[PDB]
Amino acid sequence: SMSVKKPKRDDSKDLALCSMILTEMETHEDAWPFLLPVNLKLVPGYKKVIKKPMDFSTIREKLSSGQYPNLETFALDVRLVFDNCETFNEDDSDIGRAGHNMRKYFEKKWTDTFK
Image: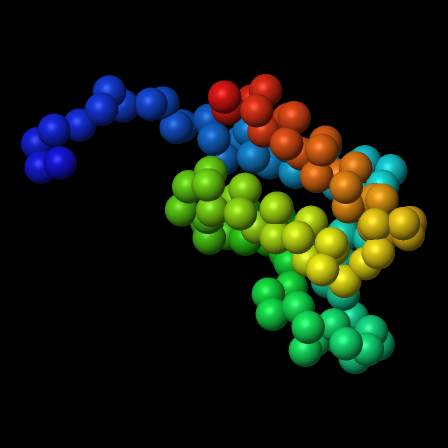
């Protein structure tokens, strides 16, 4: 509350560490469905169904331009990529399996780096 604070966590490396995670996600072999925005002219249903599209290139540009105020807003956008994927794709499809695998990969790196 006012004049009552928990001890200050060192957050000075967060930006760099989120960038490293994102690099590791970008270079994973199953990242291909997520690298670029879904083409809303060429994929029927996507525009109407997915209210907040997100992809790795869009996260990278937000990260590089100071549009994440803290590491929780960064994690929210990553998870949104996988939540969108589950909304639109069957579990038993290449893209559906890609999203489950990438989500797992991300969640481990996140825990290991920050928890």
